Amino acid sequence: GSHMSHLDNTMAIRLLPLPVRAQLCAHLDALDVWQQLATAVKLYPDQVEQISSQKQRGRSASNEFLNIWGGQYNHTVQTLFALFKKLKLHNAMRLIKDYVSEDLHKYIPR
C-alpha cells in the first residue's frame, strides 16, 4: 500500500505547531523506534545521519525527523495516522487525534 490517490485533505504538517509535536516525538523516543519511522516512509541514509547525530545531544530523533519530512516535502497528519498503525501504537494515535479529520470518530473508545 503506497498509492491512495489522496482522496482526502488534512491540515498540512506545516501548520502543526512544532512545540506541540515535541510531545509525541519525546514519547516515541522512549520506545526507541525512530528508525522504524524514517525507513517506513523510505528515506535517504544521508538524512538519517543528521538525525542520529542530533539525538546524541540529549535530543529527540522524531523531532528532527518531523522537521525534515514535515518542512521540505510537506505532508498531512492523515498519512501520519496510518503510520503508527505499523506497530499498533494505539497510544500515539489518540495522541494526535484532535488534529485529524472528524472522520476518525469511530475507533475512539466511548
Image: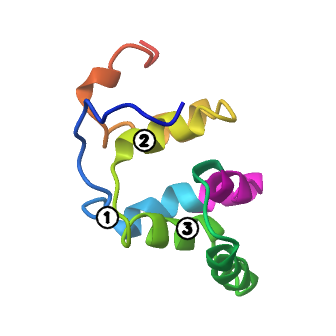
- Quadrant position of the C terminus in the picture: top left
For the point 55% across and 74% down, the residue is 64
Residue type beneath disc 2: Thr
For the point 63% across and 53% down, the residue is 37
Q: CA distance from mark 2 to mark 3?
A: 15 Å
Asked if the magenta segment contains residue 44, the reply would be no
Image coordinates for residue 91, horizontal then vertical, percent? 58, 36
Q: Secondary structure at mark 1?
A: loop
For the point 54% across and 40% down, the residue is 83
Residue type beneath disc 3: Phe
Residue 96 seen anywhere in this rendered image of the structure: no
Image coordinates for residue 80, horizontal then vertical, percent? 46, 44
Q: Main secondary structure of the magenta part?
A: helix
Image: magenta residue range: 26-39
Residue under pointer 3: 65
Residue type beneath disc 1: Pro
| Residue 105 position (above or below residue 19) | above
In front here: 1 or 55? 1
